[PDB]
Amino acid sequence: PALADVCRTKLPSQAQDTLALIAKNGPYPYNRDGVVFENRESRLPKKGNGYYHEFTVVTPGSNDRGTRRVVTGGYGEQYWSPDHYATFQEIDPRC
């Protein structure tokens, strides 16, 4: 299943903030940051257990954590999802 590409620079500032915290290894804003994402719908390439982890992308002015996420892979693949894993774009770091 071909995924859409999105340029890192075109993402919301908060998504880019997350990408920067991942590169730095936190400290993260949420306790659930870093947990395994299981890809149970096969939207990302299918891999072995624990290949993917999710990180929250801050949504200014909820009260809650919200829906926006980055998912990373085991070799450093990065994916954007604004909608709690309903959709994914592969993040292009070169634009």
Image: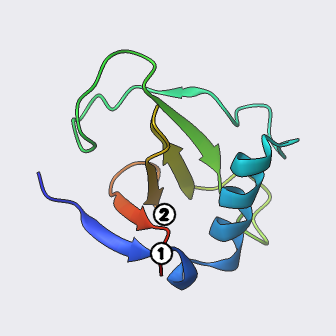
Can you name the residue that lies furthest to the left here? 1
Name the N-terminal-most of marks 2 and 1: 2
- Residue named by callout 1: 94
40 left or right of 65 in image? left
- Please tell me which residue is depicted at 46% across the width and 19% down the height of the picture: 50
Residue type of the residue flagged with mark 1:
Arg
Image: 8 above or below 21: below
Mark 2, mark 1: which one is toward the viewer? 1
43 left or right of 32 in image? left
71 left or right of 27 in image? left
- Please tell me which residue is depicted at 70% across the width and 37% down the height of the picture: 33
- Please tell me which residue is depicted at 61% across the width and 27% down the height of the picture: 35
Q: Badge 1: how crowded within 10 Å, few (<14), some, or many (20+)?
A: few
Residue in front for this viewpoint, 4 or 95 = 95
Can you name the residue that lies furthest to the right here? 27
Image: 2 above or below 52: below
Residue 82, numbered label: 2
Q: CA distance from mark 2 to mark 1?
A: 21 Å
Residue 36 horizontal/vertical position (percent) = 53, 25
44 left or right of 51 in image? left
Quadrant of the rendered image containing residue 38: top left
Report the label total. Answer: 2
Residue 86 horizontal/vertical position (percent) = 34, 53
Residue 64 horizontal/vertical position (percent) = 74, 52
What secondary structure is found at the residue carrying circle 2?
loop
- Please tell me which residue is depicted at 39% across the width and 74% down the height of the picture: 6
Residue 89 horizontal/vertical position (percent) = 35, 63
Residue type of the residue flagged with mark 2:
Pro
Residue in front for this viewpoint, 74 or 56 = 74
What secondary structure is found at the residue carrying circle 1?
loop
